[PDB]
Length: 219
Ligand SMILES: N[C@@H](Cc1ccccc1)C(=O)O
Image (tube, rainbow, N blue to C red; front, side, top):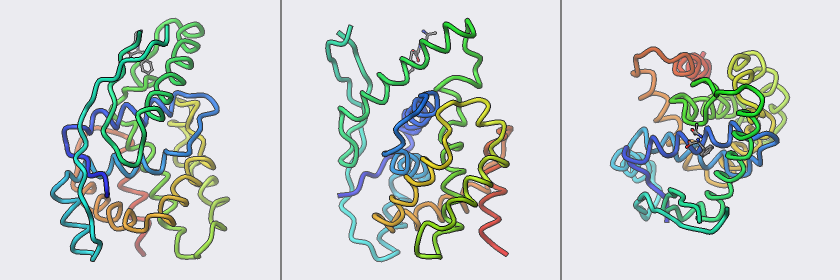
């Protein structure tokens, strides 16, 4: 069974990416999956299914809905997603860890600027820039291109790394190497996502960085 998020959970996945990005010494074990879930909510449920079926994969679609979970950790209310690939506990521990780093940020700077927040609209796209680097290096059938991925990420995502303490290229890249090796159908989803993304036109810097990195996968 594959999780097929639709456009309605896009804003939620974006905030999930940014929660990981604000976390200092963040456990990026699930970042590859979360990044792939984001691209899927940008494509939508119908396109994702069509992409997978046409590429010869037998896929059992699972609807992604927003659930409210309550747990005593103060009685706290959490907004979570119905994912077969990601438990309610994993999602809630992501929020708990990021709220700790947010509290630390508030103590140091006083008020968090919009571009330093977990709900900045470019958070999901920041994560997907690492995936664009990983995709270029998969052909070698190993992980020898990792040193080059970190080298490029430090240069191309220089401003983004100043904005987020949780933007750790080695960890995020290892997460995408594992997810593309374990679930090769995500490579098809991501390739289809990047071509549809170059059609996007707006004022986002990271949308532009992604469009440039994606075209570098050709030549
Ligand atoms: N003030 C923040 C608290 C928070 C930080 C980090 C993650 C989740 C929540 C908010 O409501 O968005």
